Image 1 (cartoon, each protein chain N blue to C red):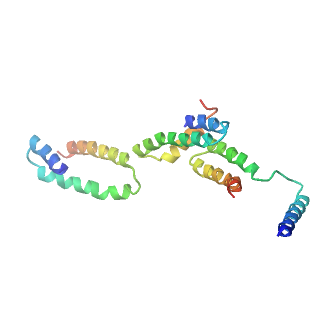
Image 2 (image 1 turned 90 degrees about the vertical axis):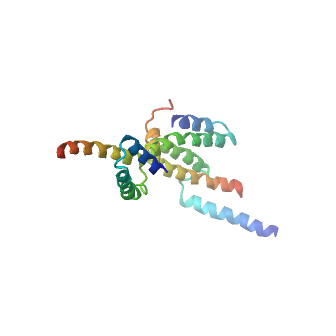
Length: 59
Length: 73
Length: 64
């Protein structure tokens, strides 16, 4: 989740088409909490939204 | 045909200036605010969600489509 | 084919009750599953199947 936070700023100040490529690479990062909660028989979209909600800065 | 576009050139200045008088509270045009508001509200998608980053992210996804279309038209 | 294999399991340990092990296993997955796999929680029903086992064990000591 934090790598997705680490890359959206890295997308934002990049410039051109590469910005959208950094962001969709961060969309591939989100599947790892997603496959676990389904395997743990829980909600994936809830749990990953909990993760990013715990934050001060991206570390 | 030059005067057809010239009339609608003048008509745009009539529409925007009458609108500028009735509301002094004026921002920039061209969807310039929306791209900021796209990134502004995805920060709330970073901030708030229990599940709401799917919605506010989609909300902020649709905001940049207007200057996207204004580039695409 | 796996129903034969768990019947081979009961046969090699006992040989009896192999008729009966396949009877009980049907309605476990017949009754619970479609109500809950439309809700899709596989792991919870596994742990529910865990706690169905040991409660039966203590109840065996109650009745025997």
